[PDB]
């Protein structure tokens, strides 16, 4: 997503992936995944409220982040 | 508090131990390659990125040879933020997208090193582990890269705790390098023995010899060919656009300027 | 053979000096190599290698980058060659009439042709005091021949 | 505006190719140290060179006194020391 | 998985038609994606309100 | 007709021309 | 001293005394 | 060259464990092997 | 903090990198 869009879009989550998720006790956490979902949703909402002609690579982001949530819920 | 706990559990912890420096360095080598290839204000930017890739690789070597997990943490944090801030300094792109991608792989493998730990046995050249043919070729290629061999030696010396000076450190490195190359050859001769007194295979000879001859041909003849080819191209039609005949007659006032141009 | 004995002697002297200095100032058995000494020599070598590859590139780019000296038409010589036999209509002007467009003037032209991207581009890319004004004279007096 | 050529040859490839060539040759120059440093550890890692400098200085002394017959003889010693590495080990022993 | 393909459509109906109803569709998706696995097995017949 | 066995031979022996063995 | 200990090698070290 | 790579790798092992006294001692072996060609012949014998 | 002892060390050892010892 940071390779297709820039600035405030991304550059918050990619930074957090490198500095929080991958630098953690085994499995990231629960708060990381929650904040990821939350940020992606907020980004979608504010891009919908208009950047113009917003792109939605955050659809595949949100849905993959909710797929992982389901995988870790089943454990 | 929470931040402190995260950092404590990233330093003290109770994890395993892996050596992913080889792969981290390979990622950075690919990054260097694509930035070098991506020369396309822009030259200045690409030159700064060069100095950067280089400096970061040197710092990485330091922390690896000094086995510093805290140092790697700091470096990772700084580098992540700085590379992401360099996305804002786009003012001097597929090349940059790929550079970001390969740097992301470096950040992922680096993060792994920090969260795993540094293994006790860190010394030892990656390509001298096995004694096959691939190891042989790769090692020789590393030695053929302009300054990699010497940089590795000096750098390692500076970090690794030694009693010897640079001269003597370089001695043991040379001896080892040569000894490895010999060992690989000895091993391959034991693996695939060559009958006693079996010519040398006509084809092998023809190949190597031919290549050498062609290389020598390209030292003398090819330059001459190229030179002549370029220089020979000469001749662009030049026709007087106008015929300006000024028949300067009067010594005092030269006149008779009846003349013509391209239509005529 | 003379050169042989000179080489041998030179090398032998250098070795002797080093041996003597090691006897004068002995180094404990197994005493690292002094972090600072390492940092110094190593650093110098690295910097020298940096100056083999990077520094030339820097110098090269620095010199070559400097480009761009304003060139404005001093005069606007419009010779409207009309008559096929005798081309005339040479009413034209020079520097006094020619007006080097100012920054404000440049903005005006750029804005006039702002809708068309490339039109504005031309004007904007050309530096201020670059676009000159062709105030060609139209008055005659010069009869024709 | 006009563009002054501050390149000389060709910034794109002429100077570029020259730069590459220089780097390579400087590469070989620097390799010239850290490649065969081990082929001299027999003429450069001598423990005590005192006996060899005596030989060398005796050649010099015998040339000042112009007894050049002994110059030939002492040169013979020098070349045999350097023709047999094992005798160098013996002659350059730290103590005796 | 049909419960979920509908959630996809809910999201994209909002996205395409940029309006206020669209923001509402987006929200309906966000919600039933979070609180959704719960009512995929609890709304099967038990009050699909 | 360069076989793969010949091809490795060639390569290794040019490497021996430069590098040791 | 470092100097004397790096210049102490002799033939006795290379004798084949059960070198496994 | 098996016996020489053992020496070389022992220098490396002794630098990782930071017993640098033995680094100096094993370096002495390396330099004497390369200071006397006849001992190299002995040490690099095919079998023994 | 380069001491004079360190400074001579540095110099001599770079000389050893080029010249013998
Ligand atoms: C993986 C990709 C490999 C290529 C990377 C990029 C290529 C860069 C240049 C590679 C060219 C390969 C040619 C190798 C020729 C072997 C010679 C050598 O020393 O190769 C050296 C490495 O030196 C180098 O830096 C390679 C470049 C040599 C320069 C030859 C290039 C010709 C162009 C310049 C022409 C002028 C030649 C020099 C002029 C005067 C120099 C004093 C390898 O022995 P070694 O001791 O570590 O051995 C250990 C035991 N004998
Ligand atoms: C020649 C030494 C072995 C290294 C293998 C690759 C080096 C470059 C040779 C062919 C490149 C096109
Ligand atoms: C040793 C000669 C083999 C053929 C040359 C190898 C490639 C080097 C590039 C020179 C152009 C022929
Ligand atoms: C051996 C490297 C030490 C630093 C270079 C010495 C001075 C030589 C001039 C080259 C410019 C850095
Ligand atoms: C096995 C490759 C042929 C021998 C090496 C010659 C240099 C490369 C020329 C053709 C590359 C496939
Ligand atoms: C295309 C002709 C040669 C160009 C570079 C290939 C290098 C040859 C390597 C020789 C054995 C690997
Ligand atoms: C530019 C990449 C081609 C590799 C340069 C030459 C490699 C082979 C030449 C001599 C073989 C050691
Ligand atoms: C003792 C001088 C510093 C080490 C030598 C580096 C080359 C000169 C740079 C600064 C000269 C004082
Ligand atoms: C100013 C940077 C180096 C210029 C020349 C100094 C030479 C360095 C000597 C290295 C040890 C004396
Ligand atoms: C122009 C004067 C500077 C000296 C040139 C280089 C001297 C040091 C370089 C390598 C040290 C032996």
Image (cartoon, coloured by chain):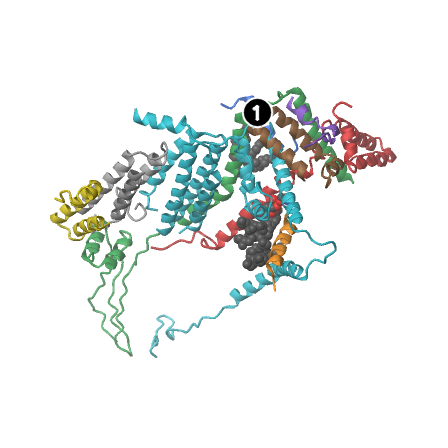
Chain colours: B cyan, C green, D red, E yellow, F orange, G purple, H brown, I blue
* Residue depicted at 40% across the width and 31% down the height: B73
The quadrant where residue C84 appears? bottom left
Q: Please state the horizontal and vertical placement of residue C42, each as a whole percent of the image.
A: 53, 33
- B244 is higher (above) or lower (below) than D90: below
* Residue depicted at 15% across the width and 47% down the height: E25
Q: Please state the horizontal and vertical placement of residue C57, each as a whole percent of the image.
A: 46, 46
| Residue B263 visible in image | yes
Identify the subunit bearing mark 1.
Answer: C
Relative placement, left or right, of B232 versus H46 is left
Relative placement, left or right, of B228 versus G16 is left
Residue at the outermost front position = E45
Q: Mark 1 points at which residue?
A: C32
Quadrant where the image shows the N terminus of chain D: bottom left
- D75 is higher (above) or lower (below) than C61: above
Q: Please state the horizontal and vertical placement of residue D69, each as a whole percent of the image.
A: 88, 35
Secondary structure at numbered mark 1: loop
| The one of A74 and D39 positioned closer to us in this rendering | A74
- B214 is higher (above) or lower (below) than A61: below
Image quarter for ligand 6 = bottom right
């Amino acid at each position: 997503n940071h390779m297709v869009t820039a600035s405030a879009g991304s550059l918050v989550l990619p930074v957090l992936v490198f500095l929080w998720a991958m630098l953690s006790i085994p499995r990231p956490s629960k708060r990381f995944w929650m904040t990821a979902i939350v940020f992606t949703e907020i980004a979608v909402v504010v891009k919908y409220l208009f950047t113009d002609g917003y792109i939605k690579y955050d659809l595949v982001q949100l849905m993959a982040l909710f797929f992982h949530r389901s995988q870790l819920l089943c454990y | 508090p929470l931040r402190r706990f995260f950092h404590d559990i990233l330093h003290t912890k109770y994890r395993a131990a892996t050596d992913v420096y080889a792969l981290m360095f390979l990622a950075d080598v690919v990054d260097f390659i694509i930035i070098i290839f991506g020369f396309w204000q822009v030259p200045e930017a690409f030159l700064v990125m060069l100095l950067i890739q280089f400096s970061t690789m040197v710092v990485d070597r330091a922390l690896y040879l000094r086995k510093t997990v805290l140092g790697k943490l700091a470096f990772q944090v700084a580098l992540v933020l700085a590379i992401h801030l360099w996305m804002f300094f786009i003012l001097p792109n597929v090349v940059a997208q790929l550079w970001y991608f390969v740097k992301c792989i470096y950040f992922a493998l680096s993060a792994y090193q920090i969260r795993c730990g540094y293994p006790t046995r860190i010394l030892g050249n990656f390509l001298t582990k096995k004694y096959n043919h691939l190891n042989l070729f790769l090692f020789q290629g590393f030695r053929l890269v302009p300054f990699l061999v010497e940089l590795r030696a000096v750098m390692d010396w500076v970090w690794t705790d030694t009693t010897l000076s640079l001269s003597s450190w370089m001695c043991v490195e040379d001896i080892y390098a040569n000894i490895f190359i010999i060992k690989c050859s000895r091993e391959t001769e034991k693996k695939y023995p060559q009958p006693k007194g079996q010519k040398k295979k006509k084809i092998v000879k023809y190949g190597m010899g031919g290549l050498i001859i062609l290389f020598l041909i390209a030292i003398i003849w090819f330059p001459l060919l190229f030179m002549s080819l370029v220089r020979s191209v000469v001749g662009v039609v030049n026709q007087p656009i106008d015929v300006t005949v000024t028949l300067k007659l009067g010594g005092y006032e030269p006149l008779f300027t009846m003349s013509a141009q391209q239509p005529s | 053979s003379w050169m042989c004995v000179e080489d041998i002697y030179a090398n032998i002297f250098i070795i002797k000096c080093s041996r003597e200095t090691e006897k004068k100032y002995p180094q404990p058995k197994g005493q690292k190599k002094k972090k600072i000494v390492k940092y110094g020599m190593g650093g110098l070598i690295i910097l020298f290698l940096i100056a083999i590859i990077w520094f030339p590139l820097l110098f090269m780019s620095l010199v070559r980058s400097v480009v761009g000296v304003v060139n404005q038409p001093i005069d606007v010589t419009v010779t409207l060659k009309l008559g096929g036999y005798e081309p005339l209509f040479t009413m034209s002007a020079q520097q006094p009439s020619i007006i080097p467009f100012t920054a404000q003037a440049y903005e005006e032209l750029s804005r006039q042709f702002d809708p068309q991207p490339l039109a504005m581009q031309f004007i904007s890319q050309y530096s201020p005091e670059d676009i000159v004004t062709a105030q060609i004279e139209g008055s005659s007096g010069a009869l024709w021949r | 505006k006009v563009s002054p050529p501050s390149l000389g040859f060709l910034a794109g490839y002429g100077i570029m190719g020259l730069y590459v060539s220089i780097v390579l040759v400087i590469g070989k120059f620097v390799r010239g140290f850290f490649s065969e440093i081990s082929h001299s550890i027999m003429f450069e890692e001598l423990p005590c060179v005192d006996r060899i400098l005596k030989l060398c200085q005796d050649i010099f002394l015998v040339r000042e006194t112009r007894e050049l017959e002994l110059e030939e003889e002492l040169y013979a010693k020098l070349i045999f020391l350097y023709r047999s590495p094992e005798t160098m080990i013996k002659w350059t022993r730290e103590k005796e | 998985y049909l419960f979920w393909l509908v959630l996809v459509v809910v999201f994209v109906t909002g996205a395409t038609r940029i309006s206020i109803f669209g923001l509402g569709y987006l929200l309906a998706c966000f919600y039933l994606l979070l609180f959704g696995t719960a009512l995929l097995q609890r709304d099967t017949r038990a009050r699909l309100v | 007709c360069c076989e793969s066995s010949d091809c490795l031979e060639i390569c290794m022996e040019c490497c021996g021309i430069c590098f040791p063995s | 001293d470092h100097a004397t200990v790096i210049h102490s090698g002799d033939y006795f070290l290379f004798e084949s005394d059960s070198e496994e």
